[PDB]
Amino acid sequence: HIHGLPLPSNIPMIEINPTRVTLNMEFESQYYSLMTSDNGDHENVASIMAETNTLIQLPDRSVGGTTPDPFAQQVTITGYFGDVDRARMLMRRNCHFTVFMALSKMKMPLHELQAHVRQNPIQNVEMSFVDAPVTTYLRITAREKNQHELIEAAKRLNEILFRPAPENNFTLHFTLSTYYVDQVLGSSSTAQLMPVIERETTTIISYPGNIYEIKVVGNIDNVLKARRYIMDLLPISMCFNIKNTDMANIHMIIDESGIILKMTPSVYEPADLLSGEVPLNCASLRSKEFNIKKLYTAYQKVLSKKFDFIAPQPNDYDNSIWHHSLPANFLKNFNMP
């Protein structure tokens, strides 16, 4: 209970359907362009929207001020709950990611390597060279679903470059929204969450605005594992409105699973009639991505049985080390916008 409310409204509400919701997730802006491009493989955002009959929006906000923009990298998916979940999965699998390989120490001259890569192009594994202020690095990029194709191409290259390959020849740059630094990495009143990932993935993670960079180092397999655990920590939330007659001060609830239900009473008072007052609630469910399977369950509970529906129980995150090694406090973010 948390004592300008309720939220008034005059625009004619066409409908107040609980099954109509928006999902919010965090996606790294450095890939926005690549999620857009029509690679002709029917996999970009447009494609997904079309096949999921949903609306997906990538932000483009230049925010400044005192506090970092909490929406710097937040993407929203809106539509029927059943389709939104399917678009959740398709946006992760199809999303690109990048990894850098240290060319230092390689036997063959760089020029020959360039020739190789230039004369052998894979359709799902873009490769390009870049020089960090002055050693050169190889940039490899692919969509999540083709992670097997990328690793192999990488491991094929090590073989070819060290006819004894170093054990920290890979680096990944994860861009988190500074805002969430306290919730992902840790805060003064919590445990430091990255050290745990290092211990479980044999990787090194160093870190220092709206964008915060987390640097991960280690073999290719471990890094992509660190990435996954880091991403399991990204916050997630689902919004929707609900007529009082359709349920099973600001209202917040925390179950013993980590989901947070926030209800903001609002009212729709017509302007053309000056009668009829439909009392409704603005709901919002939060939690960390990996715990999404428990968010839907929380959702099913708010909806009335009359809707006779079951929430989908995704399994994309069942192997998260976070289901047993994450301190409770981390899933209790009451102030999150």
Image: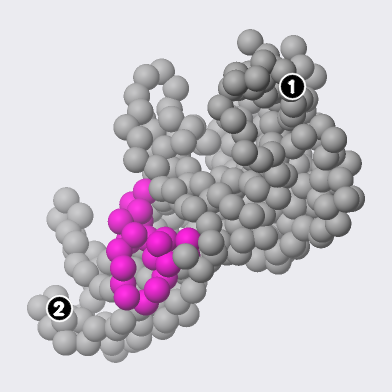
- Give the side of residue 324 with respect to residue 129, left or right: right
Residue, x 60% and y 21% (percent of image)? 272
Q: Nearer the viewer, residue 198 or 237?
A: 237
- Look at mark 1 in the image and give the residue it sits on: 277
Q: Marks 1 and 2, Cα distance to the nearest angstrom?
A: 69 Å
Q: Is residue 328 above or below residue 142?
A: above
Residue 94 percent coordinates (x, y)? 46, 67
- Asked if residue 41 is among those painted magenta in the image, a careful observer would answer yes
* Rendered position, 131 above or below 62: below
Q: Secondary structure at mark 2?
A: helix
At x 37% / y 48%, what residue is drawn?
Answer: 29
Determine which residue is flagged by label 2.
114
Magenta segment main secondary structure:
helix
Asked whether, in this view, residue 161 is left or right of residue 64, the answer is left
Q: Secondary structure at mark 1?
A: loop
Which region shows up in magenta? 29-49
Image point (85%, 35%), residue name: 245
Instruction: Give, as a three-letter code, the residue at label 1.
Output: Glu
Q: Quadrant of the N terminus?
A: top right
User: Which residue reaches farthest top?
Assistant: 4
The answer to whether residue 260 of the structure is visible from this angle is no
Callout in the foreground (1, 2): 1
Query: Where residue 71 sits: x, y (%)?
Result: 46, 36
How many residues crowd around disc 2 within 10 Å: few (fewer than 14), some, or many (20 or more)? Answer: some
- N-terminal-most mark, 1 or 2: 2
